[PDB]
Length: 108
Length: 110
Ligand SMILES: N#Cc1cc(F)cc(Oc2cnc(C(F)(F)F)c3c2CC[C@H]3O)c1
Image (cartoon, rainbow over all chains, first blue to last red; front, side, top):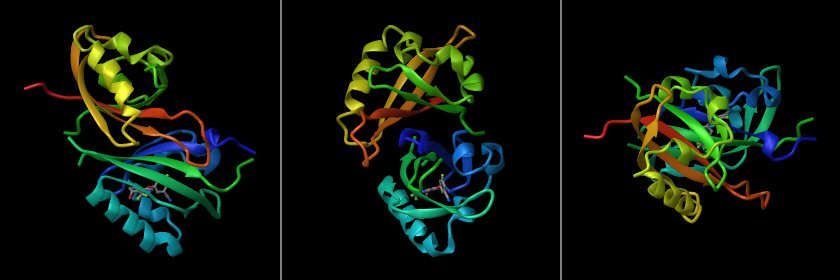
């Protein structure tokens, strides 16, 4: 089983929530290649049961500037759903969203 | 045009612990030319103190964004104006020391 650190990765997003960048660490955790994430909305990946709430986390973020998601599931690359928690921050000059993403589920 | 900009992580002293490869187009260096060195080493002597005081304050600000502007020395030997927006992260399941997450963008001073 992996340390909290080895289960933590960063993602960057435009204001529409498309990925603009993602740590390679996401590969050993969830399966995706950061390359394949760019231009796709985070929305594509949330479990239907978490979507309305992630939308409300998004609103809190845009209006307040920083947020903690609390728990949501992300569709894995090769089937199934990994639990996560994300802390989000808006960088204004709004210019982008920095996400620190922590995988709740156990890895290894 | 999107500003160029790269992400980095630092310890509370200022040492690069992680560098986004978008650094190449932004400042000229490979990630491994930054990793392990203090960001203060790449900073203009008039700006070095501001930047050390910036890293000292970002940890007292309760995870909120602190921004700083300073001149960073590219590998192409020029002083680039940098806007660095940083904040601390601390995983709330743990009591590990916080570290500092930075976005670094070449901006205009004018
Ligand atoms: N599934 C998924 C997923 C995974 C990731 F690694 C990041 C991500 O994106 C977000 C996660 N939480 C958040 C939020 F801050 F809302 F919690 C946000 C985003 C994109 C912008 C923002 O709404 C979504």
